[PDB]
Amino acid sequence: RLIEASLYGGISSAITRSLRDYLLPENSGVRKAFQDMEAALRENRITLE
Amino acid sequence: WEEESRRLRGKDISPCRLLFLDQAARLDAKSIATLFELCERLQMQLIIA
Amino acid sequence: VERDEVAAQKRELEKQIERLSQPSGAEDSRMIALAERFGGVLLSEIYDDITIDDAPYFSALYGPARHGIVVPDLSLVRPHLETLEDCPEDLYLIEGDP
């Protein structure tokens, strides 16, 4: 991504939006928390049905 | 990336720095001059075409 | 009373399962945080694929530092050390190439 963004740099490019990708880490914590919510909701749905 | 890694590398190791640009003609004389200024200040290499 | 006892058991079980859950070692907390506060890779992760047979020896050797963190420089953690009030009461730090 560093490579291609430099190759096609400047402000008027996808770079200026995909900043949030290229600069930032992917957080596993939120992923796991969402999965836990999903499990809770699944159990709730099962019980309700 | 370097701030992070230099801690995790040989203390006398300085990773190379090299970037790219296609259609470098979007640059003009002053553009070239200032980019070279900052590039040298950052001891970095250009492949601008 | 029996139901409440079983509920307590289940609560303990769930909490401990969490304790074993992610991402490597026990949890993603101050210990995993040091992986970016400095280059503090987790010891247990550093031996993630330990064989089950060496894992007991590894654990016994590493002692409480079992959950310690490898940091080529611990003089370097010194500047930030004063920040760590919210940390496990007693925190291991190790020197070497993770």
Image: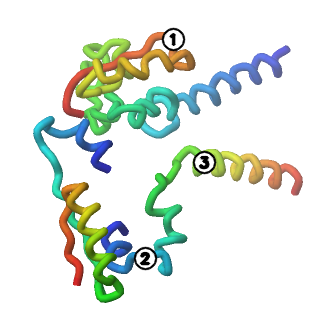
Q: Secondary structure at mark 2?
A: loop
* Residue identifier under label 2: A10
Where does the image place residue A15, in percent across and percent down from the top left?
A: 46, 72
Q: Mark 1, mark 2: which one is toward the viewer?
A: 2
Q: How many marks?
A: 3
Chain bearing mark 3: A
Vertical side of A29 occupied by A17: above or below: below
Disc 3 vs disc 2: Cβ atoms closer than 8 Å?
no
Q: Secondary structure at mark 1?
A: loop
* Left or right of B2, for residue A15: right
Where does the image place residue B8, in percent across and percent down from the top left?
A: 23, 38
* Residue identifier under label 1: C89
* Residue identifier under label 3: A30
Residue C46: which disc?
none
Chain bearing mark 1: C
Vertical side of C47 occupied by C57: above or below: above
What residue do we see at 80% from left, 53% from top? A46
Residue placed most toward the observer, C15 or C36: C36
Q: Secondary structure at mark 3?
A: helix
Q: CA distance from mark 3 to mark 2?
A: 32 Å
